[PDB]
Image: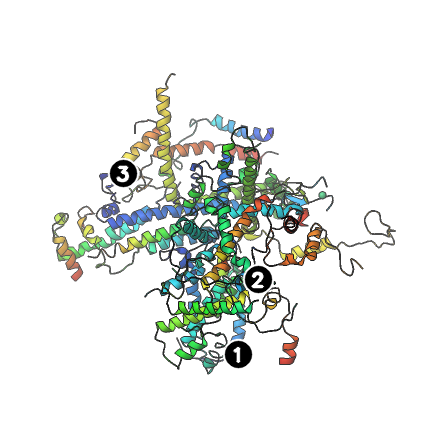
């Protein structure tokens, strides 16, 4: 019942990094589609 | 980010593409950062999991490091601990609770709004005056009239409280105003806690007794410093215990090998190490064969708990079981008598003698001795009743 | 990994969405390989109306077939009824239902008074 | 349910966040919901 | 048990640097690419036509 | 412990008697460079003009001269 | 998709035979991989109950307790070197 | 040595996208050659690149 | 905040105010006490996205200015109030919904209490492990009855154990570095160590120069973006190969001496 | 003079609620082991207050809001609990 690998992978600091990287990836995917002008 | 424009980046066709596409340049930068972090994640996972293959425990103590006492289970055991003494449990917990009440911000927003109210005494948004007008007479009896009078003296008693003690934030009884707020960042609150001595209660704060720096006096370096050092050692030992519990929760060997206690001795082979790393990987950690089968453990324990005699006790002349000495309305109706109990006998007798101590409005601090809780409250009531005859 | 705002919310939201989508696919399949008989009015009434407490009787009489209740007026009356029930249950939690305090806690919180089995089996069953 | 100290802090924050007819038909349980909720978060 | 965590880490980061950040589909993708201006802008610096 | 350390010292003294390169023929299966042994060449992606400067600085440091 | 509502009382026996989905004890003799060493039958049962009752907290609480196990360690009442003894514990 | 001295993520990703751009979709030289090219001065801002591109879109 | 989940976070902890066995041990104990506090503030479990907060906060705050359906709304409202009662009272037959803790989750994890607990710096022993391992190898040895139980036997099993351990460690290292992101990590660390070695070299050789007889283009972009086969001399490859071949040159003779001995 | 409880502290939420907030009538007989006049008056005041808050006759035109003549009968007991908790430091030896 102690899921050490998943608790380590989903640690709050790593979750914060994944949020930041998802923000940057979504912003740079939008910037690249809305440049169709 | 404006980079990849000079001659120093001439030669790669994809870089030649990224010259005129800033979105490609930004995609490259973000992707390189993400790839580097993924490499960090892979390496950290390897560095976490590969030492688990190298851990081997002692086969005699099964990785415990302590064995059951040879005698008595004493001068061969360990030296107990601080918390085995049952007589000091309530005092230790009372001092710990008094220390934790400094840090406790469970009533945080309530004390913050009280602090704002006592800071700006110009509030508004009342919108209806409470009626709340019935302290009827100093006459009649019962419980309702007494509780209602004690509830109606709330304003004057609160004024007395705010005059004698004031706000906890204005006297540093609590942590103060907004210093540790969640949702800000783990690290801004760490900075605010490291600011002055916010991690210590004022009973151990160094900036409270430095004014007594001449000649020592009340032992600001021998009593307050000793108390602060003991408190820090206790919280560090709590962190060690939590790390040991975390390692025990995932079946891993414990990192901190604690000394043997009053029922245990050190292992014969380890001496207390109980496990260690080695060059040779563990073939039980690998292949999943680390824990024994339940039926095998049951068979081992049954055979160990049920010794058999293969000699009839008539040919061998044995008439007694193994051991020394050999020849030889209580405990069968009610069953035994408590042994750890007995220090609470006086408090139980006083609670039976005075049923008013069972009042729901009364909350004593707690304790068993003459000093603390029920006996302290009874002595205070008796002293008040004796001194009201002289006044 | 997922939508931006926080990963601490979208992960339970995704788990809840997976569970409810699995429930909604388990349903509509047991209404096609086992379509509803009058059970659709029997098990959706009575055993559901019993779970509906008091303080909703007024809004159930008014909005349903007795009057009209708009959209936000209906939601406002439902909120008022829910808060009346919430205050009633807070009072039932501390001072009890229409019974004394020696039954509000002494026999209820302290789990004395063992459940009625002899009386509920002989007199009823 | 018995709240730990952190969950008590969450309760105090929720209660202190939340908000931010004839007398006859008025329910007998007509008390101040916020005051009772906060007096339950304490004690 | 020893090999899946690497796949989990790789997939978890692949969702954020390939699925969301930079995709790459096949087939007819003319009208979506401004890259071809630069691509035809460097054709004389690429291999002799053949 | 002296026997184990003596075995390790005997191995080290054998390596000392080996000393350098003298007495050993050149081997066509084992050239002195792993890039010769394998097939590792730089290609179109990765090589850039500034890389010559960086290569010059790394080669200066590897040869042991403090010039760049 | 289809509307062929077949009726048979052996489908209850087949659903009971889908206890292998719960326990994964058939996996080694069928594939070679002993998935019962890593499968969580309690978590599968909680997921099944959550799906059946439309109450996702039943599965989510167990999953979060499995993931954040360290935060489930006793942090209340264990303050500052709370060791008794082996002998006092006995 | 052969494993550690191998292309990393940046070099591998610049090897498939670079192939896709300058190697797979650079086959449009045969298209633009059968319709019209000048090359050479098709660099810079000749303004025939725009006409060739819109003719490629129109097909 | 940026270096939170990394081993390079226990180096910022030593750059705080005073916060006050050696002084380094006292500072570490003080930092462990600072981590123990702010967990005793009981703010770590609070999350703005908890279902508990969405029960009160986002239910009074959403309305704002701005069977069937009715008995599907009534039951939903009753369930919401039931969860609110469970979160507050001794309500029964209600199960709560948890939240992901994201603040100060395990304060005891990012601390090195080992050197303090084992009574180092004030002033247990391993190696029963390998003795027990080789003893078990000898005591069981699997018996090579197919070679009619030869005399050496234990030597063969010990050689197999050493070979398997060495090969497992080397295979783990090779499989780890076979990942391209791990190669990116190695490249980044090599660049950092090169620049820091240049700093060391600058300082040291400048001192031993005056003591004799007494921008991103150059700064980590053209190195981070280039194939490291390009910017690496063949001199260092030849040097590493020569060092390796000089170290592992007596292996045949030492193997023959060990196996041909007693 | 030392730390001890008091009956004037009124630590019981049941006391603090049957006296100040909750005023209902119970009809049953006891099986296992309070100024009704005042209670009825307080209940009627409570009903008038709830009614007024329901027809939005208050300045704050919301049915439920946060009053700020904050209850002394609650703030005082919170401060009493904090004082008795932090004054346990003098309960040593
Ligand atoms: Zn042992
Ligand atoms: Zn003993």
Residue B78 or C85: which is nearer the viewer? C85
Q: Is residue I242 above or below residue B46?
A: above
Horizontally, is B49 left or right of I209 in the view? right
Label 1 residue SS = loop
Which one is closest to the eye, mark 3 or mark 2?
2
Horizontally, is H12 left or right of G21 in the view? left
CA gap between label 2 and label 1 equals 71 Å
CA gap between label 3 and label 2 equals 85 Å
Instruction: Name the residue beneath numbered marker 2.
Output: B145
CA gap between label 1 and label 3 equals 76 Å
Instruction: Name the residue beneath numbered marker 3.
Output: I217
Q: Is residue B121 above or below residue I92?
A: above
Instruction: Tell if the residue under mark 2 belongs to the same chain as the one under mark 1.
Output: no
Residue B57 or G30: which is nearer the viewer? B57
Residue C72 or B52: which is nearer the viewer? C72
Which mark is drawn over residue G9? Answer: 1
Residue B326 or I26: which is nearer the viewer? I26
Horizontally, is G31 left or right of B381 in the view? left
- Residue I213 screen position, x and y as percent: 38, 16
**Classed neighbour count for the residue bearing mark 2: other residues with Cα under 10 Å, few (<14), some (14–19), many (≥20):** some
Which subunit holds the residue at mark 1? Answer: G
Outermost residue on the bottom side: it is C38
Image quadrant in which the N terminus of chain B is located:
top left
- Residue B142 screen position, x and y as percent: 61, 63
Instruction: Tell if the residue under mark 1 belongs to the same chain as the one under mark 3.
Output: no
The response on whether ligand 2 sits within 8 Å of label 2 is no
Q: Is residue I47 above or below residue I242?
A: below
Label 2 residue SS = helix
Residue occupying image coordinates x 86% and y 50%:
B327
- Residue I177 screen position, x and y as percent: 41, 44
Label 3 residue SS = loop
């Amino acid at each position: 019942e102690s899921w050490d690998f998943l608790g380590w992978l989903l640690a709050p600091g790593r979750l914060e990094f994944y949020e930041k990287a998802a923000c940057v990836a979504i912003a740079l995917r939008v910037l690249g589609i809305v440049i169709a002008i | 980010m404006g980079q990849f424009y000079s001659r120093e980046f001439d030669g790669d066709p994809y870089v030649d593409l990224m010259r005129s596409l800033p979105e490609r340049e930004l995609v490259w930068w973000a992707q390189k950062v993400i790839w580097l972090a993924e490499g960090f994640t892979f390496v950290d996972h390897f560095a976490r999991t590969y030492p688990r293959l190298l851990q081997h425990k002692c086969q005699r103590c099964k990785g415990a490091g302590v064995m059951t006492c040879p005698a008595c289970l004493c001068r061969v055991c360990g030296t107990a601990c601080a918390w085995d003494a049952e007589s000091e449990w309530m005092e230790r917990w009372g001092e710990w609770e008094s220390r934790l009440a400094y840090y406790d911000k469970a009533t945080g927003p309530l004390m913050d709004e009280w602090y704002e109210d006592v800071l700006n005494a110009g509030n508004l948004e009342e919108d209806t005056p409470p009626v709340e007008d019935d302290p009827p007479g100093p006459e009649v009896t019962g419980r309702w009239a007494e509780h209602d009078r004690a509830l109606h003296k709330d304003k004057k008693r609160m004024a007395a409280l705010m005059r004698r003690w004031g706000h906890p934030y204005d006297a540093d009884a609590n942590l103060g105003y907004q210093i540790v707020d969640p949702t800000a960042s783990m690290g801004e609150n760490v900075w605010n806690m490291a600011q002055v001595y916010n991690s210590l209660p004022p009973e151990l704060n160094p900036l409270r007794t430095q004014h007594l720096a001449d000649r020592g006096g009340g032992n600001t370096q021998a009593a307050v410093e000793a108390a602060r050092s003991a408190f820090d050692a206790q919280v560090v030992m709590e962190a060690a215990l939590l790390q040991n519990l975390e390692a025990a929760a995932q079946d891993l060997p414990k990192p901190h090998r604690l000394p043997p206690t009053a029922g245990t001795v050190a292992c014969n082979e380890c001496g207390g190490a109980a496990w260690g790393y080695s060059f040779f990987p563990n073939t039980a950690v690998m292949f999943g064969l680390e824990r024994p089968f339940w039926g095998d453990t049951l068979a081992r324990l049954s055979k160990y708990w049920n010794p058999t005699q293969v000699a009839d006790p008539a040919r061998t002349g044995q008439l007694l079981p193994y051991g020394e000495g050999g020849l030889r309305a209580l405990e069968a109706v009610v069953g035994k008598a408590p042994a750890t109990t007995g220090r609470y006998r006086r408090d139980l007798e006083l609670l039976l003698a005075h049923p008013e101590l069972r009042d729901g409005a009364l909350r004593v601090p707690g304790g068993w001795g003459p000093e603390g809780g029920l006996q302290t409250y009874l002595r205070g009531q008796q002293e008040e009743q004796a001194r009201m005859q002289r006044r | 990994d997922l939508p931006e705002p926080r990963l601490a919310a979208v992960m339970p939201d995704a788990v809840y969405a997976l569970v409810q989508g699995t429930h909604k696919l388990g349903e509509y399949a047991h209404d096609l390989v086992f379509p509803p008989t009058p059970e659709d009015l029997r098990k959706l009434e009575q055993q559901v109306n019993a779970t509906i407490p008091r303080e909703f009787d007024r809004v159930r009489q008014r909005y349903a077939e007795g009057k009209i209740a708009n959209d936000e007026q209906l939601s406002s009356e439902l909120e008022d009824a829910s808060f009346n029930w919430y205050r009633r249950q807070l009072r039932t939690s501390v001072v009890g239902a229409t019974d004394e305090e020696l039954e509000d806690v002494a026999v209820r919180k302290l789990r004395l008074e063992p459940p009625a089995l002899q009386a509920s089996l002989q007199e009823r069953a | 349910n018995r709240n730990s100290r952190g969950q008590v802090a969450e309760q105090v924050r929720a209660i202190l966040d939340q908000y931010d007819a004839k007398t006859e038909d008025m329910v007998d349980d007509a008390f101040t919901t916020e005051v009772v909720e906060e007096a339950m978060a304490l004690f | 048990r020893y090999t899946v965590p690497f796949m989990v880490i790789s997939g978890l980061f692949w969702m954020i640097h390939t699925w969301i950040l930079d995709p790459l589909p096949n087939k007819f993708r003319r009208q979506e690419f401004i890259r071809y201006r630069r691509e035809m802008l460097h054709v004389a610096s690429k291999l002799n036509f053949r | 412990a002296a026997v184990a350390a003596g075995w390790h010292l005997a191995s080290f003294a054998l390596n000392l008697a080996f000393w350098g390169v003298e007495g050993m023929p050149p081997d066509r299966y084992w050239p002195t460079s792993p890039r010769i042994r394998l097939q590792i060449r730089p290609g179109r992606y990765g090589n850039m003009d500034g890389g010559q400067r960086v290569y010059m600085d790394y080669l200066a440091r590897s040869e042991g001269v403090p010039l760049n | 998709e289809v509307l062929l509502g077949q009726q048979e009382a052996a489908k209850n026996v087949a659903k009971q035979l889908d206890e292998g989905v719960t326990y994964m004890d058939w996996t080694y003799r069928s594939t070679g991989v002993d998935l019962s060493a890593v499968w969580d039958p309690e978590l599968w049962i909680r997921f099944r109950e959550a799906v059946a009752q439309n109450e996702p907290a039943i599965f989510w609480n167990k999953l979060l307790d499995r993931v954040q196990y360290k935060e489930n360690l006793p942090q209340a009442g264990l303050v500052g070197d709370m060791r008794i003894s082996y002998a006092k514990f006995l | 040595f052969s494993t550690i001295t191998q292309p990393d993520t940046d070099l591998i990703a610049r090897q498939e996208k670079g192939t896709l751009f300058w190697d797979i979709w650079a086959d449009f030289l045969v298209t633009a050659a059968d319709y019209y090219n000048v090359n050479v001065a098709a660099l810079s801002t000749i303004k025939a690149e725009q006409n060739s591109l819109i003719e490629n879109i129109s097909n | 905040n940026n270096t939170q989940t990394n081993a390079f976070n226990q180096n910022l902890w030593w750059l705080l105010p005073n916060l006050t066995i050696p002084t380094a041990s006292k500072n570490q104990i003080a930092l462990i006490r600072l981590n123990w506090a702010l967990n005793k503030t009981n703010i770590n479990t609070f999350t703005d996205y908890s279902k508990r907060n969405n029960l009160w906060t986002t239910q009074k705050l959403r309305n704002q200015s701005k069977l069937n359906i009715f008995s599907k709304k009534i039951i939903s409202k009753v369930k919401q109030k039931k969860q609110k009662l469970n979160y507050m009272t001794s309500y029964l037959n209600v199960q709560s919904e948890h939240n992901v803790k994201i603040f100060h989750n395990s304060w005891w994890t990012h601390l090195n209490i080992k050197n303090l607990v084992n009574n180092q710096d004030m002033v247990f022993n391993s190696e029963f492990i390998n003795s027990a391992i080789i003893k078990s190898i000898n005591n069981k040895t699997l018996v090579e009855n197919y070679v009619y139980s030869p005399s050496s036997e234990k030597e063969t099993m010990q050689l197999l154990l050493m070979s398997s351990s060495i090969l497992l460690h080397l295979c783990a290292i090779i499989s780890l570095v076979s990942i391209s992101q791990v190669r990116c990590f190695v490249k980044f660390h090599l660049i950092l160590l090169y620049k820091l070695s240049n700093v060391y070299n600058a300082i040291l050789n400048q001192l031993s120069n005056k003591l004799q007889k007494n921008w991103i283009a150059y700064g980590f972009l053209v190195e981070w973006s280039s194939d490291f086969i390009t910017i690496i001399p063949e001199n260092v490859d030849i040097y590493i190969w020569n060092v390796f071949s000089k170290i592992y040159r007596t292996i045949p003779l030492s193997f023959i001496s060990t196996t041909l001995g007693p | 003079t030392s730390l001890r409880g008091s009956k004037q502290f009124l630590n019981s939420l049941t006391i603090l609620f049957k006296h100040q907030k909750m005023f209902k009538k119970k009809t049953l007989k006891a099986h296992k082991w309070p100024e009704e006049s005042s209670l009825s008056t307080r209940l009627h005041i409570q009903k008038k207050r709830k009614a007024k808050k329901q027809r939005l006759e208050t300045r704050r035109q919301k049915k439920r809001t946060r009053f700020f003549p904050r209850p002394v009968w609650l703030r005082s007991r919170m401060f009493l609990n904090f004082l008795t908790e932090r004054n346990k430091y003098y309960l040593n030896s």
